[PDB]
Amino acid sequence: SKLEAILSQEVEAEIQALLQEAEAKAEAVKREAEEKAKALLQARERALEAQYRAALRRAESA
Amino acid sequence: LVEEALRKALEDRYLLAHEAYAGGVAALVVVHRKEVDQAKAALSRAGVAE
Image 1 (cartoon, rainbow over the protein chains, first blue to last red):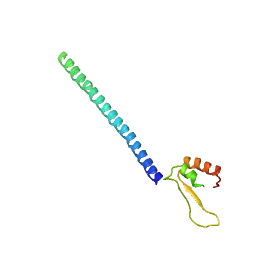
Image 2 (cartoon, chains in turn yellow, orange):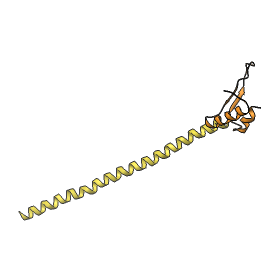
Image 3 (cartoon, one colour):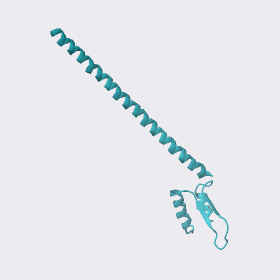
Image 4 (cartoon, one colour):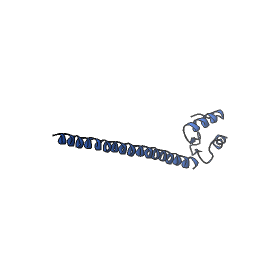
């Protein structure tokens, strides 16, 4: 039947829209997780090198 | 006479027939919600009752 095929089309269209929305969501999720992890790694070179340099400052002064 | 509205709807759709029990012919028409409600209004304009 026509509406046999049309309800099959509706199920396929809702599944395809569902998975496209899920693709956009998963891409934004891996984007935000990678941005947070790289903000971590960018902050850690500051948080470690500043400690190392201040240690050499006070060691040289001592 | 009632299937003119079904042909006015989607023709290869809308399973619409009368099986048996000739005291009153059980004209059942099944398509959808909204378009079937519009076609049911058109059939009641042609003369029909749920």
